Amino acid sequence: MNFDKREERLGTQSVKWDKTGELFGVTDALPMWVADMDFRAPEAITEALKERLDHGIFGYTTPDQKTKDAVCGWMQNRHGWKVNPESITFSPGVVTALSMAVQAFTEPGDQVVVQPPVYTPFYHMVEKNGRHILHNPLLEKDGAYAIDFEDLETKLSDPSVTLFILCNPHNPSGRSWSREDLLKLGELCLEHGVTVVSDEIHSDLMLYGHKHTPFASLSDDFADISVTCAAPSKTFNIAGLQASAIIIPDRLKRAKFSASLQRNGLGGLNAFAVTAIEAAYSKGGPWLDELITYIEKNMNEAEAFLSTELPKVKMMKPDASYLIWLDFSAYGLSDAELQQRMLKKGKVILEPGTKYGPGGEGFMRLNAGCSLATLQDGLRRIKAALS
Amino acid sequence: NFDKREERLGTQSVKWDKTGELFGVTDALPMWVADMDFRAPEAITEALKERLDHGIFGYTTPDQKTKDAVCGWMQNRHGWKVNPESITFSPGVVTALSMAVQAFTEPGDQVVVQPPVYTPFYHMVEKNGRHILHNPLLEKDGAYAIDFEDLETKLSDPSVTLFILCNPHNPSGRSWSREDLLKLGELCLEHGVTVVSDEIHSDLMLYGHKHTPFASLSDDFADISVTCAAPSKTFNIAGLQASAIIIPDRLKRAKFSASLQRNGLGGLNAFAVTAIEAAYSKGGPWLDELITYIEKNMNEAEAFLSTELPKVKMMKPDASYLIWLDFSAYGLSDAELQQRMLKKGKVILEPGTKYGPGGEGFMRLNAGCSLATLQDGLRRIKAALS
Ligand SMILES: *Cc1c(COP(=O)(O)O)cnc(C)c1O
Ligand SMILES: *Cc1c(COP(=O)(O)O)cnc(C)c1O
């Protein structure tokens, strides 16, 4: 493949490139914010979409035995994890699945534990459904995030806590939790009667031979209290297609999740979604393995550059994915001022760290899912941003 | 060109590939679920190729020119002025109905519908802890009419908060008159009921029938209505999951958005964003060519039914490609009618059962197909009835 190839994305109705005016107040800044890549989907996906377009009929389209086998086959090949086809419910996206899972496995007024800072919709899919966020803040220990197990046990044992949403890899930072972290979390959740939603959407994008451990893979018991959200969207840059496989080995939990879909008038995938998730999990491998190497070399360049040129900026090197959580605390600036210096003076758009709630103060997130050249330009824009 | 023979077996089509699971047969001609056996308009497939060639499928959002396409259609096809601020995108009309029910009622509230009607109307009320209240349709002159005296009684009940209008009405394809709609609006305005109008059959007006959007009739009506429109039935693209929901009243639009956010919805897929624009922008003449082919298909059905199966009363539909067929005069049970159709004739209709009360003795025949496929359908219906 050829990730250095320069793409024009202006005028493609791209949220990342075309909605900067609406969302940031600038038209002339390099977009490096929302988590989508600047790359063409693999040819293995587009071949098969063009094939679906050629048939020319776009009526009611359903996933089938071969769609499920591509999901199962992929999880066994990439992650060593056995999934029965029957475990899989499709969804138009993982944020939808987060919402459905909240509605299915908790009551109005329950508490849901998350580990902040974290992906913003975790807050929204709990708060907007009249459930309550209880935070288990992560600890910064040695330029990497660690889980605080003493706080978690205190939080998980309150009787109104019925759900825990795990982000693994964690967004932001790209932290890949250890087997032992998951085992400790799992046992606490069994003990305290807490269903686990595992958001594993970044889990294919593992850097430097970091190993992903799907929570549900660890025991029967874990499998029976888990809802794993997986998707080709981050892995193959096809968020645009609204395709998710949600894995729920417990029949009763699956039926409750399905019921939430039915109630809200959902359960269909669009016809392109159905082609895309079969092609992606069938023939995506080789392209992913070239993307990892490409992202590794992008991450080595950002680390090289910041530690040399910007020594007050502290970069968490991610274990996975193409998003870099960056610490600008040392500059003593408001989040309001940091962002204006990036927007007006560097001409670059990063995600402001306050988006991710407590612990996001003084950080911003940088989308390194672009050609080396675009990354080098953006790094220079961050330096420029700071006098 | 609608006479081209089109292969749909092996294409993950619910209609053609899910018969074994849903009807217990794989050797029958499927003429049940409401999608067509035709290629979409070239105006949509050509714009789809453009987005495919660009080769990147990240987060894609509707823009002003998407909402303009929608306002262009409603102005050009209907004479309805729609401000872009009024449009909220949804992945589907069933999704919209669920959202409307959750946004505009309380649990325990009663929701009026006119049976027999599209099955999801019942599910999206009952499954959400709301109560279906029937305003049954009367058969008069072999066509449906509204029972306004019964309707007035029911809209008066104070726990009734929502009316779900099907216009055109599935099943039957009935296109409600200006007069019908003015009287319905008056009652809901009188009794503080919110009107959800499913208008998804509204662009396939046959034989000079004219669709009247509820919302178009006055500011009073606009402001209590939720209009669910889509290109999906009109252009055979239900599998691109695109729809446009028109809420002129800003407060009800806010509550409807809030139901979409709450459910982690709001986004359209990249192809839907393309498809809805192209369809409402450039689909006009392909649709006129389709109205004409449907009209021929209906004429053939009426001619064949009046001559070869005169016991069958066809409701000639005002709109869409779905034929509501009364098999009463045969005296088979609903269950024997379906086993005869599926096992003897080896053809699949929608059993009128599923549409609720007023549905017994009926089945719905899908004529959205080549005249050849329809003639094979009618031949199999006659074989089933011997
Ligand atoms: C980007 C992202 C998502 C997005 O899910 P969709 O399927 O695109 O709705 C969900 N979770 C995490 C952690 C993400 O980073
Ligand atoms: C087919 C049909 C629908 C389904 O709409 P989607 O866009 O597929 O959700 C809704 N309403 C009526 C009356 C229909 O006939």
Image (cartoon, coloured by chain):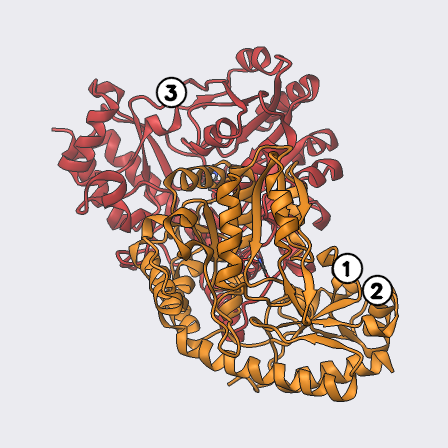
Chain colours: A red, B orange
Q: Are marks 1 and 2 in contact (CB under 8 Å)?
A: yes
Q: Which mark is residue A359?
A: 3
Residue at the front extreme?
B149
Quarter of the rendering containing residue B67: bottom left
Q: Residue at x 88, y 70 (%)?
A: B331
> Which residue corresponds to mark 2?
B334
Q: Secondary structure at mark 2?
A: helix
Q: Left or right: where does residue A267 sit relative to residue B277? A: right
Front of the two marks 3 and 2: 2
Q: Left or right: where does residue A168 sit relative to residue B58? A: right
As shown in the figure, which amino acid type bears the numbered disc 2?
Answer: Asp
Q: Residue at x 46, y 56 (%)?
A: B214
Q: Quick one: label 1, few (<14), some, or many (20+) residues within 10 Å? A: some
As shown in the figure, which amino acid type bears the numbered disc 1?
Answer: Thr
Q: Are the residues under marks 1 and 3 on the same chain?
A: no
Front of the two marks 1 and 3: 1
Whether residue A251 can be seen here: yes
> Which residue corresponds to mark 1?
B353
Pick the front one: A184 or A238: A238
Q: Position of residue A109 (x, y in %)?
A: 58, 20
Whether residue A92 can be seen here: no
Which chain is home to disc 1?
B
Q: Position of residue B353 (x, y in %)?
A: 77, 59
As shown in the figure, which amino acid type bears the numbered disc 3?
Answer: Gly
